[PDB]
Image 1: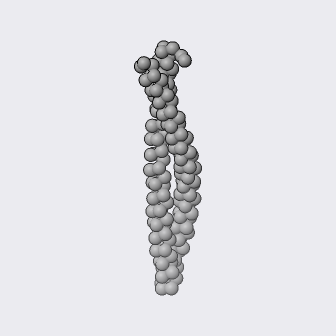
Image 2: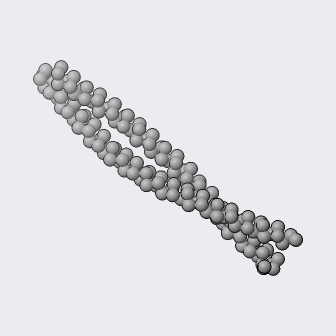
Image 3: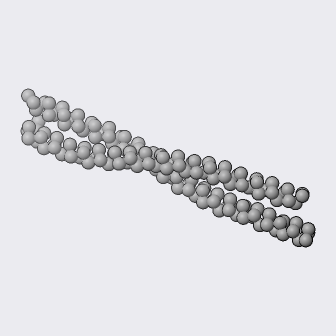
Length: 75
Length: 70
């Protein structure tokens, strides 16, 4: 009777857990890619933050000391 | 096979595990939307920072050259 309906629902519920579990493993794998890429992108920035500051600082000094040359020369 | 009661019990368990699992899924999926956007933020920051550091290095280099020359 309605027993069979219940057995159908029960079996139906189980297969949706299986499917939700495939989907879960999928996203899970995606997240590991993103975590790995994000952490590397962040290291890239910091390395670029450093190097940019070093170069710009290196440019600022030579510009400054040139203004000291031109002044000293025409003074 | 098994009594009508046993099916009822197992269906009961099955719907509890399911609600539980459905909770872990939506949140890892939320975590998937956040990481993706963050990832896109990082790529845009690395884009702009290169752009900004690139434009400054040149202009400071045009300065120093222009000064050395004249």
